Length: 101
Length: 93
Ligand SMILES: [Cl-]
Image (cartoon, rainbow over all chains, first blue to last red):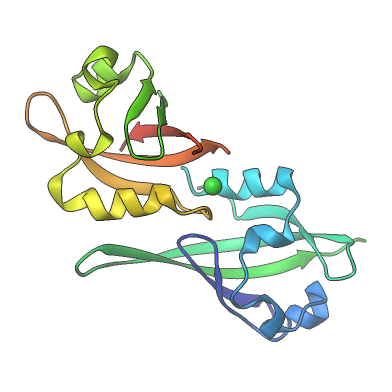
């Protein structure tokens, strides 16, 4: 199964599915409430934030697992935009770890 | 095509690149020293002030700028480099 997640527009993890533990080394409750950029090196922070400034491909970046080692993750992005009093945006992710062969 | 701007922590425009004229209708000199709020659609003032006060970002801030000719242009802006000044890049959508 893909890992499913939701981010607030500011990168805070609102939701991630429980298979975060298998693939990323974190229980879903260790990640929800934290910012995605906490689990990335600087190169990857810039890579991912750049993605949202302009897409032909999913967002591919290195994630630092709980054990401090990196995995490559490919993230399919959908934005839900809702216009009420202010316009608000949520990011829906479908992610998978790109495994070494 | 990115407009580069630097804002003081109170929103005062410290610097804006020369392509402000092209995209926004104002020369740099007409904007530098003014508050960025002065140029924003009045409805987008909470949204933008709040965006640029906050430390954590992922998505750009999308808002309306009022050009010199009194018409709207939509732009997105992102913190470009991080009493700290904010360095932002922005572009017309
Ligand atoms: Cl930032």
